[PDB]
Length: 260
Image (cartoon, rainbow, N blue to C red):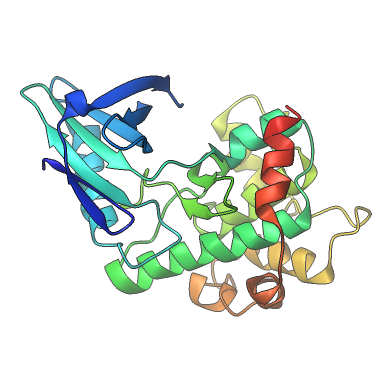
């Protein structure tokens, strides 16, 4: 408590040193008046729900243990007052869900490539360094900034259609601009489709690489038995192809945010 550590440089700080630039979507965009630094601040009210206050505390514990993972949002510090805790986090430009809403259609494979590399490495790091299997990988969990960094959101970072499956559905939704269970009226109707219907694979007519379609087919393997672990996805050729390959995520992002 009492410090913001940004870049490798530590500053003494209190909550009043921060200027509220408004809600992001209870994460605030705040400016550290001392420096000009613009950060994200989660506010946890002491009067709040006890279960979800325990989640925030467990999520923070993991975040603080993940300094060495570039693919997870980092914590700069915390402030504790009589009624609140303020958690200072890396600021990111937007999440993939908002990014799809703004775009109003498909996100290009090259972007989803860099995205998949970052998110699978985050999810592998969580499993192999903290014994966490992340429940729900959704587009709202995937953050991007205008330096082209992609990082996993810290929500639920401490937990027959979760994990690898949820990443598969995330990628189809973003690659097509269409949530595959769009026309379902209830969560129950959705679970019905997952169990009874063929997996919602990528269309064959959009110029998606074999690697991308293969990757998604593997995530959407219905049978728990034959369904791959983060360990194996981390070896998939879709990952090998985009892991090394150069993609100007920065310009692409700026282009989008400017044109919308």
